Image (cartoon, rainbow over all chains, first blue to last red; front, side, top):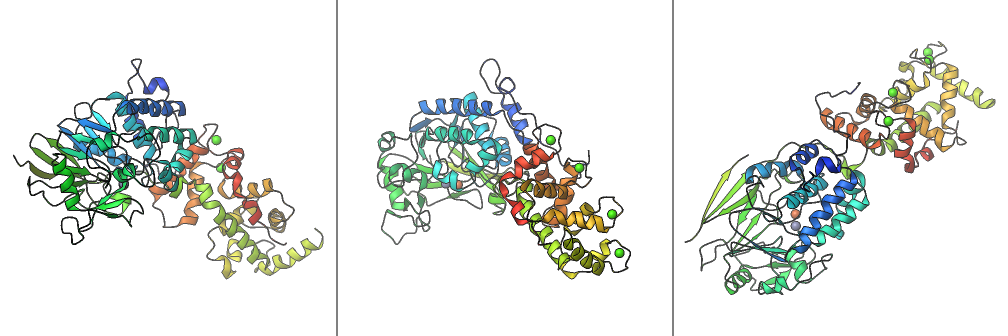
Length: 357
Length: 11
Length: 155
Ligand SMILES: [Ca+2]
Ligand SMILES: [Ca+2]
Ligand SMILES: [Ca+2]
Ligand SMILES: [Ca+2]
Ligand SMILES: [Fe+3]
Ligand SMILES: [Zn+2]
């Protein structure tokens, strides 16, 4: 054909069918899915729907607060960076033999959010007892409508795929207790959550509210000066996020000793190194809080490393990795006609005006 | 019993 | 048009520097307001119905009459399609769409980036699976843009 840049591979136009994706035992073929999605292939829409809703029925049966054994690989934000998610699985271990816990923010910002969701939901269907997914602040209607996810679904699939995702996101658990030692959440603590029972009591099956404990678990952050406070305030309103709170070092230590925990493992803030360890608890000598962030070269500009945490009896191995190549997309998943046509219109008309004048 | 942290790159 | 042709005739003779009876690319490029317009070479090629490289008077008339106020939506969409269909066969191919976009974007995209977004636009718009874009497929994609409204000249 007359295709100019031959070296560039061409996405497949064939859309994967139900028999290609699911074998006759009901198990997704994740290898086949991985290869197709890496090529910017699509599923038939009914097949994407089946993955989304079958994942959601597994999520719906899980508790608000998950009980997760060591060893486990704990991952922070992904934000639609599907090609880095492929590398993450190499760094962290095969889901076939590694327990995983993801801490939310699978979608928005990166242009491959639906591929991340289809892949992780497929993995959840295949490994229901060893792969765990928490809710992040982006996994809701309000943010995906303002950021890119709703538009991504409209252009790649349809709004039914979007609506099914929104129902699936409502079923995501809010928190995990890992190795009976760590509380894992996307954002952090609430002035209304003093015990683990306070998490178990929540009704999670809804759009996150604008305030309250569910909001706080997904949205709160440590103080900028966490550990080095001169504000004896445990929870101060989070003016950067516009909701929820900043929590202080004494707030965290209070929660930890009250509940006999070692640390809070959370995500939600980008880190140059892919992780950050905060001030040690004096009772234990271990960081009171750790942020993990798993999106390398975030937004294609931060130039950060990503990391995951591989926790195993008596050792926290933090494993860093760098970004991988990914395909180009115009803003808002615009096609080249929509992008260029107004300019074409004005430039032809302008030519003729100058010729006729 | 203070657990150890080991940080390595993969890349 | 009777006197509209006569007025176009005036501007035509003024543009035809070497009085050949036809307008060369060089003769359009003599107007300084066109020198930085990356679509001039596409418009000339479209007006140049016989492919000889120059615009004769009949070619000039019929080209300019595509931009009248009376012209309906479909007619303007046709002209816009012709912009992309370099070989005039009725189908916008991957290579054509790349080359025409390249004229407009310049150095703002790498070749690999431009090729990737060309491929994706074609896959999304290609209802009949031939890897090319027909006029019907084109209208389905750009239908809601109202660009016909902004393709008018008082002749
Ligand atoms: Ca001449
Ligand atoms: Ca000619
Ligand atoms: Ca053609
Ligand atoms: Ca076609
Ligand atoms: Fe995030
Ligand atoms: Zn977040």
